[PDB]
Image (cartoon, helix red, strand yellow):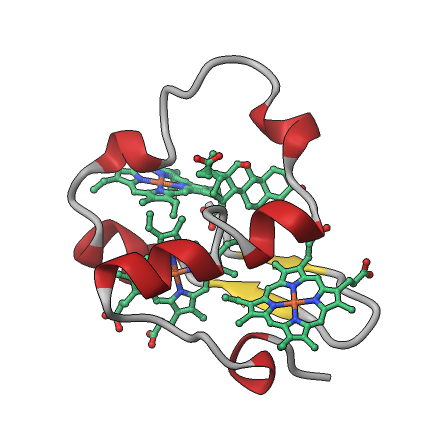
Length: 71
Ligand code: HEC
Ligand code: HEC
Ligand code: HEC
Ligand SMILES: C[C@H](CCC(=O)O)[C@H]1CC[C@H]2[C@@H]3CC[C@@H]4C[C@H](O)CC[C@]4(C)[C@H]3C[C@H](O)[C@]12C
């Protein structure tokens, strides 16, 4: 499968899967979640534990606006 880009108005956000599979061996961080996780994602989740928050907790990954968002 291909990587996906989230079309944030302020700038595209790339999500590179390979880096995540390598750095996050605990796959159940994102996979086998109960239903609702597709409908649930949004800015609040992204800037929280959906993206940014995990980067902060794991001490690696982009945490600045311009590191995630890029036109
Ligand atoms: C969230 C941060 C994830 C983590 C951690 C892991 N995966 Fe993942 N996976 C995630 C998304 C959003 C997607 C679809 C979009 C994309 O960029 O691919 C996937 C996709 C997969 C796939 C399909 C890949 C392909 O066919 O090329 C597989 C087989 C998969 N994910 C498995 C997997 C495993 C085994 C993980 C742990 C090591 C893992 N993923 C981490 C989100 C996230
Ligand atoms: C943990 C549960 C994570 C979630 C959820 C998301 N990310 Fe992540 N990401 C995580 C780690 C531990 C790392 C470091 C990987 C490395 O080897 O450097 C990353 C990295 C990224 C990157 C940069 C990848 C690179 O090759 O440098 C990007 C661009 C990124 N992450 C984006 C991203 C987005 C958009 C997410 C939500 C949709 C997201 N991550 C979730 C851990 C986790
Ligand atoms: C990655 C770890 C991010 C960081 C760091 C920041 N943002 Fe973000 N933001 C991210 C994603 C994946 C999304 C899309 C959510 C979705 O619905 O798929 C967003 C969203 C926004 C938005 C809203 C965009 C829209 O609704 O079209 C804005 C205005 C925004 N982000 C701005 C922003 C700023 C100013 C940041 C630094 C303080 C910042 N983001 C960090 C991922 C990430
Ligand atoms: C469920 C995990 C982990 C966050 C959490 O614990 O809730 C999060 C992390 C990244 C999230 C994905 C980001 C890209 C997609 C954004 C879409 O708008 C909704 C579907 C996708 C595919 C999301 C599904 C799900 O919302 C994921 C996989």
